[PDB]
Image (cartoon, coloured by chain):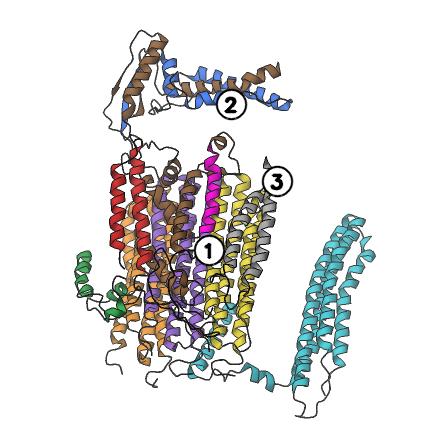
Chain colours: A green, B blue, D brown, E cyan, F red, G purple, H yellow, I orange
Amino acid sequence: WAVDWVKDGKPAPGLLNMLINMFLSPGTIDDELYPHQAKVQVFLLLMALV
Amino acid sequence: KEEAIFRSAEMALVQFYIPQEISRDSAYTLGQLGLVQFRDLNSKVRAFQRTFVNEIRRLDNVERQYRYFYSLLKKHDIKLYEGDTDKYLDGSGELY
Amino acid sequence: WCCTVLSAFGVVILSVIAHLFNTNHESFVGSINDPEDGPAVAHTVYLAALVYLVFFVFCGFQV
Amino acid sequence: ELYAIAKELDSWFQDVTREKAIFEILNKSNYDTNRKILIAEGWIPRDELATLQARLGEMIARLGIDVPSIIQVLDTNHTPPTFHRTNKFTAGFQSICDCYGIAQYREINAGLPTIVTFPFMFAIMFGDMGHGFLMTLAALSLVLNEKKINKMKRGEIFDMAFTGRYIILLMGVFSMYTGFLYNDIFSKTMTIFKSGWKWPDHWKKGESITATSVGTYPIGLDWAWHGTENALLFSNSYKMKLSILMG
Amino acid sequence: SFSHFLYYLVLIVVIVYGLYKLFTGHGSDINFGKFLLRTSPYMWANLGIALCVGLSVVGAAWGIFITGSSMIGAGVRAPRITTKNLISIIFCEVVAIYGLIIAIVFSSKLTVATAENMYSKSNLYTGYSLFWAGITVGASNLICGIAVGITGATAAISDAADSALFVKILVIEIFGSILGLLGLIVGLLMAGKASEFQ
Amino acid sequence: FYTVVGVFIVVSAMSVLFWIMAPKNNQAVWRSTVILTLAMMFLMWAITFLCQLHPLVAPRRSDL
Amino acid sequence: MTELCPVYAPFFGAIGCASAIIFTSLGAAYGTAKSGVGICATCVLRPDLLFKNIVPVIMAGIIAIYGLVVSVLVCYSLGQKQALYTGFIQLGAGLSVGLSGLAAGFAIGIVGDAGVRGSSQQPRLFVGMILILIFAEVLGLYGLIVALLLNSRATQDVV
Amino acid sequence: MTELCPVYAPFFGAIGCASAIIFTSLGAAYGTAKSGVGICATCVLRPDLLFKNIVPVIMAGIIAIYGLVVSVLVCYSLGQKQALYTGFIQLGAGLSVGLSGLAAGFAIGIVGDAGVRGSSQQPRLFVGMILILIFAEVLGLYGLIVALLLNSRATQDVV
Amino acid sequence: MTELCPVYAPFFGAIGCASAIIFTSLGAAYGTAKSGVGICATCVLRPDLLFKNIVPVIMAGIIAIYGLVVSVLVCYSLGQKQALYTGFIQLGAGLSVGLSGLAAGFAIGIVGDAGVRGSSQQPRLFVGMILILIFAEVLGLYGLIVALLLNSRATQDVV
């Protein structure tokens, strides 16, 4: 919500999409939320699984 | 200077050194405080070997006469007339 | 017995929506499907409010 | 004689009911006939030991029993029960919370957060101003007459609602809030606050008209959303996210 | 059961066939309307006239033994009930009378159309009207026959108890027969307006 | 827009004020319940405003 | 009548969107019926345990909640010009969630009846009954997650 | 017949409208039948709570009202020039509400029977009966929500 | 759409992905419901042994895990212009994992309730219970590898 998406120019992810997209693999498919936002979360995922 | 609903209140197990003679008054008042339970004691034996059996049976008998009064009174054309006064005193009365 | 609360609500709520009709409010009147005449339906709903006021007066017999 | 006895019979019954419990309780005390100085134990609130000792001493002085009365605290190896000094403000919430299960010996009783969360969780589910307001009036019907209803049989007219006077009141005021923040007196949306989306000022007889985000509606869902073909989608996405975040 | 598995097989094969046609793009090739139009309306009309009387007779006979068997069983203890209850059988077979009348009035309507000519609106309407008017009359007759048979059996049992009980239960039979009258009237109303097979 | 942070500041100030000025008797219940009312009210208002902060969809209809 | 967007495309979408609520509703109804029979049987004898014992019916209502969420989510992707892919995926998601919820409803009802019966006599079977109901509910949760994935890509870069 | 508006489009909308009342009427019929059987069977011993136990039949009547409202509104949605898509969603709404109502009616019947059996024997079970009947009703309520949302969606942006 | 990749190709994939979770859910639900009836019947005598005799329900949980993981992977394998071959093979994988899990679930349920009934009496039967549960879970395990290895070739060198 915080970022005005269309004015921001970068694509706006779906309403409830990013996490279920992430379920696949650390290779974030597309439409990153923020710089490395879809990338650094692999750290949280690996922390949970370990 | 008392506990609140923040968590379970500070419990305590205190030992009642009740004098034998004054036991009835002590129990009556202690129950009047509405503040104490009694830990289950000497319950390993059956219910008809208690030291209190005779007073229990006579008072239950008394409650039966009172019920018989109430039944015949309901049969007759009359009802209770002092319900309000008795309940208020015994509800949240003081130590007296 | 129960008609008292119904009469009171039929005063208050029916009156506020009555005035909100009479105010030619978009959410209630002016749409393609609703009746276009604001004050016209406002008159009959005000009459309903008045008859509920009388009904509330009648139900005030609880005393 | 029946008219005479009827006056005291009602009070006599509630008087005589005392000794049954009295002797059933001192039954646990193990007062042997040969034994003297009866010895027994019971659960007390720790913060009331001094006051119960004072009351017992006052009674002993009143009873004239020359022998003093003493009491000592044991080593509580056994788990003592859990207590909550709830007032009528929150007794209903506490009881409803503990219906699921009595608390652990000293744990953080879940009643206290539920006091507020349960009414608001209900309200975020309920929404409407009008229905909440009528049910709040119903709650007031028992809150205001609490003195009268306390001494009149609950029966099937109220039943479990006998204690629900304050629960229903708080969920009703939270229903008020959810109405302010969902903007619907019953179903219909209200429009006191500043105008939201400005759909284009020129419209055809039956044209499909979008809207312009000229600003943000300050309090709650924008009233401009009402009646629109995208209203259901917008509101649903909104309140999915609201539900998951609050949860 | 093997029969239930047969129903499952039929359902799955018809569903898969329909899906196959839809996906290959010939969903129109399963044209129910074309099938209705091309089949001869004579077939519908005659199936209707046959089935109206057939179902009327089936319901009549069903109610006849339903009432009669219990009537004979109750008559064993007291044969006072036989003649006085035969009215239940009479009201059961008035349903068959209705079926016969609807059959004859329908057979007033069949005839030869001018070859492929007049294979059009009038005769098609007449064919479908005759078909499901016959189905209406026959099925309504069958079901009211079932109802009147059950009520007549109950009336027999009650008559075995008391005389006046039979006459107070006969109203149940009358109410049951109203269903057959309604079936007759609806069949006549919704069938008559169609002309003959010009 | 995005004054939700400032509204958080003001509701936090109110929460701290009520935290210090608890009712004299039965302090714990007021203490917990009022501050949690305020916090939960603020959160649910925060979502209901943040949704319309920069919306991705617009109302659409064919009605006057 | 586009090749990728045939006119009969939204039939599957509508069927899936409905089935997502029908099958979940059937599962929830069977669950609450069995659980309610259990509740009545235990509470005619042990009235006080009623409110405490109401949870299995809640967990039956879970299936209905899941059906509602998946149905409305599928509906928001409906469209007259929608491609055959979209209808296909909505149909699949609806069937998946609905039948998963139906299985969850069977499990919920059966174990709710059994656990209510058991807790009628013995006091601390309730926790185990609750956790078994938890597993029965999480079954429907897996169904819902699958349905959400399908619906999430129901309109992903669809031609 | 427009390619997007075939002549046989009204079939699906009409059958949806029909099912929307047919299936809910079957469900309410079963619910009322089982509930009333229980009522008359168990209150004969003790009659005074007949009016109290009337309630499950009231719930079944609410189910019938649910079917009535969905059916009347989808009727309001019917037309001649309607698009195949419109017929598809009307059919979907009708089936959703009808079958959800059928499930709700099964729940009403079973729960009401068990509840009245218990309530005639023990009074405090009445409140729990009320609660379960509410749940068996909100099942069909969810079905109604799905159906009304569908048949609202069945008209906009239609060519 | 080309005849290599027909417009209806995603139907098989969608129905396979649905049916995988559907059938594993039915199998796991039957297993957990029936074994939970067993648990409720046994723990009224032996409440303490609940935490030990709980295993078969968890094993049905692993069956559900199998179903979800296969379903989500084969769902990620979808796509509008997917090759007919991909749809066929992924339908095969979905049905394989689903029905293998269904058979495994029947085995888990029957073995589990019988074993817990027996172990109510005798303690050393617990290890045999567990052993038979693994030798039944290997069925869903085989389904897991079969479905995964089908998925591996689902798009390997596909055109």
- Residue D35 at x, y percent in the picture: 32, 11
Asked whether residue H155 is in view, the answer is yes
Label 3 with label 1: CB-CB less than 8 Å? no
Q: Secondary structure at mark 1?
A: helix
Instruction: Give, as a three-letter code, the residue at label 1.
Output: Tyr
- Which region is colored magenta? D127-146
Give the image quarter of residue G92.
bottom left
Q: Residue at x 45, y 82 (%)?
A: E21
Residue beneath label 2, please? Answer: B84
Real-space Cα separation, disc 3 to disc 1, in angstroms: 30 Å
Residue beneath label 3, please? Answer: H47
Q: In which chain is the residue bearing label 2?
A: B
| Quarter the N terminus of chain D occupies | top right
- Residue D16 at x, y percent in the picture: 48, 18
Instruction: Give, as a three-letter code, the residue at label 3.
Output: Pro
Residue beneath label 1, please? Answer: G30
Real-space Cα separation, disc 3 to disc 2, in angstroms: 33 Å
What crowding class fits label 3: few (fewer than 14 Cα within 10 Å), some (14-19), or many (20 or more)? some
Residues B1 and E123: in front is B1
Q: In which chain is the residue bearing label 1?
A: G
Residue B50's place in the image compared with H50, above or below, is above
User: Do marks 3 and 2 share a subunit?
Assistant: no
- Magenta stretch mostly in which secondary structure? helix
